[PDB]
Image (cartoon, rainbow, N blue to C red; front, side, top):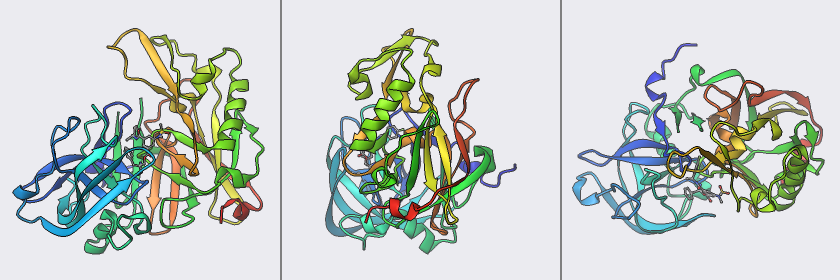
Length: 379
Ligand SMILES: C[C@@H](NC(=O)c1cc(C(=O)OC[C@@](N)(CO)Cc2ccccc2)cc(N(C)S(C)(=O)=O)c1)c1ccc(F)cc1
């Protein structure tokens, strides 16, 4: 009910749908930058040269504590890619833990389709494990450095408030950020924050697919990915069920593919015609699962208005993927997500800031009985 972590509350911002970032100050004297909170990768990288989309950048020559690692780094993602030089410097998070650590920093000097115009962030904070760090797992991720050099508990939690702001509690959990109970799912393996989905429902209706399909390849949590990305087959079955569940109004095919937008007169969006979506996650006890349920307010994202007009345009934010399921902002904006690294688990609870209406709310409920959940994972 109280909050010893109060100063970290509301420490995140976003330029409405383009990424949640936190201020991080690197080097000496201080150089503060807006850094994208990303749980889908493991490199701490900051723009280090002028870019059209960058208002400011890291200037290594002005930092007396900067140390060159004399090694380059290249990082390509599903979307965008960048190249930089590796080094280390002192790093603190003003509205984060009260510590300063010497961390690895990749100075971004060149990039393609990575930075986002108007997003207001100039770097990325990869919060995932060393296994997926580039060039290799010997480049210690920022959080690993934090835990090794300080006594900050090995845990962080995220509250991404959609519509843009939120909180990144480092080293603990803050009760004012969620309601109800926290339900935990095992981190299957320490590389990406991999989890296991055992069941999927649309408006309470089971999609009825072997659970292996839901995590075909893998299922991860990535705060730096906009949508709820699903394996091809799952996406197709999900779209058909959602269409059938919202038949009171027809939409062009391109809407479901994210290629077309639909706009309603300001404040008229018929949220009620769209179904809620539930993902069941492996629990912490044998044959026990729990489910998280999002509303259309989460998977139907607002598109930067033409100029504050009377037209609310939306994009269907559930898309397909060829690299497994990716639970992005669409999922996270409905909940307070606890990345309990110490106990190799991720917790979910209803967010105190998720967008909902007077009829429905996002939810986290359990427990449920689910057999053979172990088989759901891809080997
Ligand atoms: C910041 C931005 N991310 C993207 O716009 C993005 C990134 C990646 C992606 O591949 O990201 C990989 C990465 N997250 C791994 O860590 C790195 C990354 C971060 C920022 C920009 C590009 C790539 C995939 C996709 N998709 C293909 S999508 C349309 O969502 O299906 C979108 C974003 C995140 C949270 C929000 F609330 C709104 C906007």
